[PDB]
Length: 141
Image 1 (tube, rainbow, N blue to C red):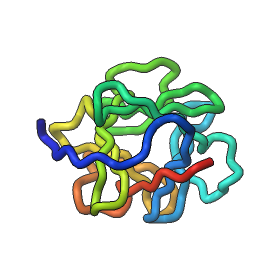
Image 2 (image 1 turned 180 degrees about the vertical axis):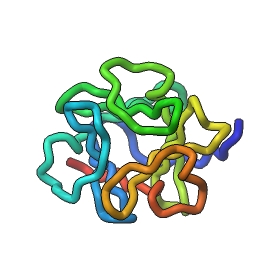
Image 3 (image 1 turned 60 degrees about the vertical axis):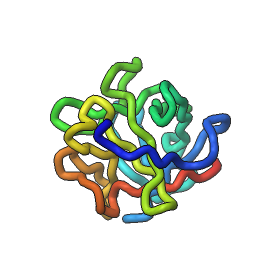
Image 4 (image 1 turned 90 degrees about the horizontal axis):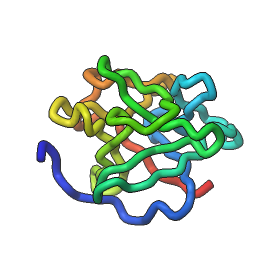
C-alpha cells in the first residue's frame, strides 16, 4: 500500500460525529451534497455512520440523508447519493490518537478528508500528512 496500517480502535456499530480538533468542527454532509464543518453539535447532518468495506476502508454516510462522503477527482469532498469508488476512505489512526481518512481512490496522492479552521473542507491535494485539518476524533452521537 501507500500508507501505514495503524487502525483506530472502536467499531462501526453506532453512528459517530467526526470531530475535527483543528477548528472544532464536526464534519457535515449537507442535504445538497456540500460538505463542511460545523461546531453545532445539534446539527442533524453531522451524524455519520461509518462502515467497513475491507479492513481499514470505510464509507462515511450521513445518517440523516444517506449520502456518502466522497472525494471527487479534483479533491473536493461531496455527498454522493450512492457509494462509488470516491466514497471509500482509508481510516487510520494518526498521532496515536486521531482518525484520518484518506481517499482510497487517491490514496497514492495522500488526499485526506480535512476541515480547515473556518469549517471549510480541504481540497485533497492541499492535504498531507502532518496537518491538523486531517485529524478527526469519532465522538458518540
